[PDB]
Image: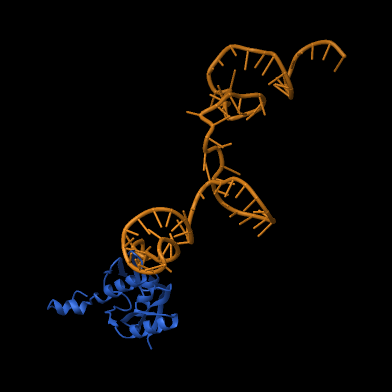
Chain colours: A blue, B orange
RNA sequence: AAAUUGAAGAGUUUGAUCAUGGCUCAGAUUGAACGCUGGCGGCAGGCCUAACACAUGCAAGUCGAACGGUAACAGGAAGAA
């Protein structure tokens, strides 16, 4: 019972001897809403087939996120090719302050309160890749506590 | 007790892509102006330009418990109706 969200549909084209060959690419994201989120990207000669391929690729290749009561553990920075992403944990009641692709990722991921901002290029594919890379690199107090070989009294 | 609890993007270069990069938009705000329209009230605001020139009226008077006074109006007055 995971939530699936179509982020962007784009029409690309390859040229051949006869003319242009138009195909469609769809970027989606799925997530169970409590710390697991994955994005899929499918190209197809039609829009529904592209969305189906994106959903199948997104249902696999899902990552785990260490949430903290529905928000981030700490401010994180995600970077892909052109997009640089900043996410920050907020208090209860603020919502998701983020761009379209960031909103989709953080909403299907299970994040409820976050202050986010996208720098550089706002390309949807690179934005969702940067968001996923920033969320999977976010660690919890138990992780750092066990990695430091000392109790979790820092929490 | 409270008195920083706060951060959104989109369109456009290409047959298509990523990046760079500028232009434009979505938000607030104003001593505002113009166009169409216009019922009431409360609170505020109202020459941003020519520190250009000014008709007219007012905007700095007051004290007789400082003084010599009596010109005006109100009285007291002696004497002539």
Number of marks present in the image shown? 0
Q: Residue at x 28, y 67 (%)?
A: A81
Horizontal relation, residue B66 to residue B70: left or right: left
Where does residue A65 sit, x and y in percent of width and height?
28, 79
Q: Residue at x 31, y 72 (%)?
A: A131
Tell me which corner region of the image, top left, top right, bottom left or bottom right, holds residue B52.
top right
Where does residue A146 sit, x and y in percent of width and height?
15, 80
Relative height, residue B67 to residue B9 (above, below): above
Q: Nearer the viewer, residue B16 or B70?
A: B16
Tell me which corner region of the image, top left, top right, bottom left or bottom right, holds residue B7.
bottom left
Relative height, residue B7 to residue A37 (above, below): above
Horizontal relation, residue A20 to residue A69: left or right: right
Horizontal relation, residue B27 to residue B58: left or right: left
The answer to whether residue A49 is seen in the rendering is yes
For this orientation, the residue located farthest to the left is A149
Image quadrant occupied by the N terminus of chain A: bottom left
Where does residue B30 sit, x and y in percent of width and height?
51, 49
Q: Residue at x 33, y 70 (%)?
A: A127
């Amino acid at each position: 019972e995971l939530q699936e969200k179509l982020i962007a549909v784009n029409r690309v084209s390859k040229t051949v001897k006869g003319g242009r060959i138009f195909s469609f690419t769809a970027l989606t994201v799925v997530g169970d809403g409590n710390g697991r989120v994955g994005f899929g990207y499918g190209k197809a000669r039609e829009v529904p087939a592209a969305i189906q391929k994106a959903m199948e690729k997104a249902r696999r290749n899902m990552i785990n996120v260490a949430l903290n009561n529905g928000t981030l553990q700490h401010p994180v920075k995600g970077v892909h090719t052109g997009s640089r992403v900043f996410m920050q944990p907020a208090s209860e009641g603020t919502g998701i302050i983020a761009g379209g692709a960031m909103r989709a990722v953080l909403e299907v991921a299970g994040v409820h309160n976050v202050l986010a901002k996208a720098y550089g290029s706002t390309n949807p594919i690179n934005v969702v890749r940067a968001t996923i890379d920033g969320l999977e690199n976010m660690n919890s107090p138990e992780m750092v506590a066990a990695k430091r070989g000392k109790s979790v009294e820092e929490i």
